[PDB]
Image (cartoon, grey):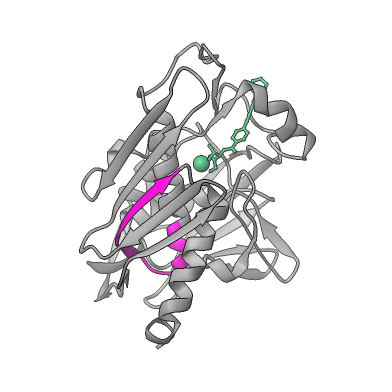
Amino acid sequence: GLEKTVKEKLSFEGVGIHTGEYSKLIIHPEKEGTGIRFFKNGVYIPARHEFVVHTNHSTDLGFKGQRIKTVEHILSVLHLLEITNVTIEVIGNEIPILDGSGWEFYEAIRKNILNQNREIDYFVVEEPIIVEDEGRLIKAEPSDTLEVTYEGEFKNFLGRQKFTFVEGNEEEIVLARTFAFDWEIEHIKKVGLGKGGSLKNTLVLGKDKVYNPEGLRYENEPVRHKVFDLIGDLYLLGSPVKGKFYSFRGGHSLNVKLVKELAKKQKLTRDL
Ligand SMILES: C[C@@H](O)[C@H](NC(=O)c1ccc(C#CC#Cc2ccccc2)cc1)C(=O)NO
Ligand SMILES: [Zn+2]
């Protein structure tokens, strides 16, 4: 498809899930060849793996002393809509979490797309690859379309779940919310994170129950969200991606490990 930007500036705002601080975004149109980048305090931070500074419970980027936490959800939405040129100005320290899903970003951006004049140079996975870490695994292989499967094995009533995204089914993952388990939240807070987490933006699960009065949006909401996360992290390759991916219990750290291995393989087709 064609490279795309946004027609008009778009703004979003609200608390960040990890900092608990209120932040604001302004998404700016950009010309062909710009790529996706963030902007904070006069500094541009490209949405690329080289700028990753943290991957525990979120994917965070930084450059020249400026940091932005939790880029994965806005990047996933941009990846899914194939927005390729845009500046995300951040006033604050984190992307707003909103309702925990990509829905608000997705609906607003989808109605505000501007087609541009050259085609997208997709990052096309050229051969099979597997990355592993402590029982977790992610595999990628060539595909003309983006296909992403996540399989989880949860230590509560959910047990084993898997979900597969394919192109055309974007609406199946952009409403799936971030989630946490009650027995893990104390640790997360103790290590300086989750300060903005609440039942308003997080699906909170116990061994045998759901805390949110509204319940789950889908019986497999957690693995839908994990697919959504992975698609955001994959955009750190710097272009929309064509490939078939399977993640078993993956998280941001493993996702970024995969991205870095893929990028290394193709640095001399991509940089040209
Ligand atoms: C999903 C995973 O990949 C990941 N999310 C997290 O790791 C995470 C961690 C903690 C919290 C939280 C919280 C809370 C709370 C709370 C609620 C009610 C009362 C008191 C505290 C949310 C997300 C994620 O979505 N990355 O994109
Ligand atoms: Zn997430």
Q: Is residue 193 above or below residue 261?
A: above
Q: Is residue 16 above or below residue 207?
A: below
Q: Is residue 171 left or right of residue 180?
A: left
Residue 214 appears at what percent x and percent y? Answer: 45, 14
Residue 164 appears at what percent x and percent y? Answer: 29, 42
Quarter of the rendering occupied by the C terminus = bottom left
Q: Is residue 76 above or below residue 40?
A: above
Residue range (magenta): 234-248
Residue 177 appears at what percent x and percent y? Answer: 46, 32
Which residue is at the front of the view, 96 or 145?
145
Answer with the quarter of the image where residue 200 lies. top right
Which residue is at the front of the view, 131 or 13?
131
Q: Is residue 168 magenta?
A: no
Q: Is residue 199 left or right of residue 18?
A: left
Q: Is residue 171 left or right of residue 129?
A: left
Q: Is residue 24 visible?
A: yes
Residue positioned 66% across, 22% down in the render: 183
Residue 51 appears at what percent x and percent y? Answer: 61, 67
Quarter of the rendering occupied by the N terminus = bottom left
Answer with the quarter of the image where residue 35 lies. bottom left
